[PDB]
Length: 126
Image 1 (cartoon, rainbow, N blue to C red):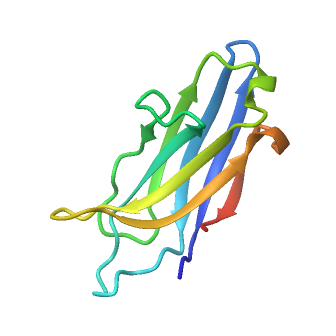
Image 2: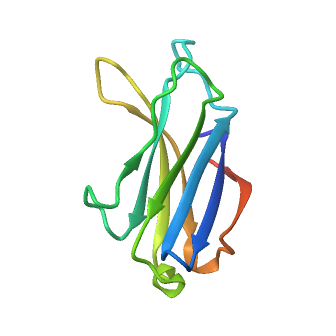
């Protein structure tokens, strides 16, 4: 049962050939079963590429259901049309210190159909 939402800004700058991705914050995340809060961080990939090259990761925020990162990532070497057919995959994870980290939810953006104007928007975690 996934719950919560993520606030993202997506911009594209033709003058530098860069897709600009800002993860502002997330809100409304569930607690753990334990009742403990989560320690959320996000991973971002520009798919289909799954190598270290495409990977970005936010800092981890401690014990909270309302993490704020204010973190901007840049993907270079892209014409606007190169984004067609690619997906921005943002996944939230709960940092577990002594075990595998738990999947919280994801937002996947079909860039071909996005305006990319750096407007902050909210996306339901899926």
